[PDB]
Image (cartoon, rainbow, N blue to C red):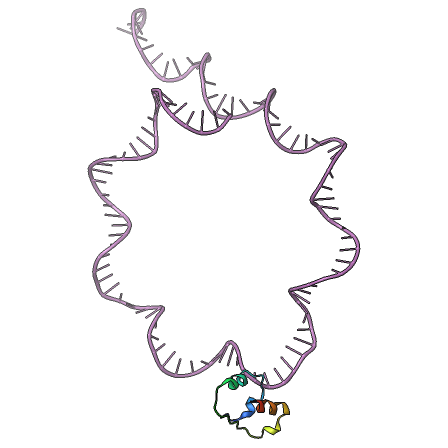
Length: 48
DNA sequence: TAGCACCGCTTAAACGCACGTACGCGCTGTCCCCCGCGTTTTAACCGCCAAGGGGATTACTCCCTAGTCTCCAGGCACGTGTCAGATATATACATCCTGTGCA
């Protein structure tokens, strides 16, 4: 689980890459109101 | 022609040995500072936010530069002559001996 997924928003960040590499069986992303953000970040999250 | 070898005097630098003394080491007590450790503070990076500047590399294009052969005539190097210095030895008395005439 990731809380406050809005912090993930930048796929260019190193933490985004690290998190993506982490082997997991299921993933849950929790954030208040991501839809506020530009489409690009939404795509990033969906790619995650 | 510069190094090698043997001659063979002349010191003097090495050497053995003697005495002592002041230096190095063993042990002392002291005390202060720098380690082992705990708590606070600072320096640094991630991510924000994505670039523009300007720098090093790369190439083309003359052209100027001194690599080249060559003559001219020299100024620099190899040597001999001259001048000076350090060494050598007479001298004008220096430092004295010694028979003998004088007090």
